[PDB]
Image (cartoon, rainbow over all chains, first blue to last red; front, side):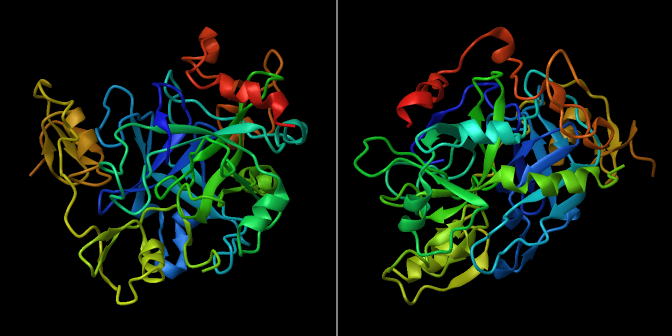
Length: 259
Length: 103
Length: 49
């Protein structure tokens, strides 16, 4: 995450990390919706342009982490995946439209002071929170700077990172890029000359874009860090999967006879 | 330009650029090509120079010896050692049975 | 599970344990504590529009 600050302990109890098996590297991030279901961005598992189509035997999940590298024994829970569910109309060839995927932990995990699920937004909640100018949270273990070792020091975080970013009006999102924006994706960020900065960056893919309903004081996941044009660039914005729109499909998967 | 060869997914899939440099993923490796480095080509996946292979299991130090056998037939010193092996030494390994591996 | 007031959306049997008590952080919400930059969000629920 670009232009952010270290996270606190227990700030994102749902912040899941997608770790590749061999090599032992970071892939993306994800979210926890129940003791057994985990949500990400499809392009983290299936992205043909990179000769990439990972199966369960190709990755591990890691939850309850803070430092992105040390095996935090006291709290970290590692999991194997039972099933991967990529959205049937994930448009990877043109603009990652419907860039989403569900994952089922091969064995339910234990919740704790460091492990808790985010709430998915309902229609009413989508109504009042999703408004240009309102802020949401992005957290991740991805790059802190753009071009791998770009300007100050190392570009990888030691601990989880966070930034709070503003939702942007659709016309501005559409105007900023030459890619076919769809209704299944919103963009966020600070306008140029608005002072503040901050953005997602290579490594954050799949990370939760969260909002806190004042209505019930709970945290909801509106989107999923998907794609963008460079990190923290002027006049460009970060694009997230509009989760609420695709909720109908998650319901289908989970409830169409899971177990 | 016109915002297209640099739009990319924020996924990590490190590759080693021919210019001796590591690229976040094959997309950025291309964007660089479209901004001055036409000669740029990939060479192999994985960073050019290996990462600082540190002490991930650094927290299992001092753990009392209590061996357990992992699904990989490697007798581990203790659970903690084993758990940690799964994110490093033996990706994904898991407890087969307590006590030394039966051989 | 319909707890003291939540609106669960998925089936606990197929979904798993969570939803009912979701989005209420054990270390924060539960202890009425706020995080460093939390308020930034509650503040945008006005000047945003």
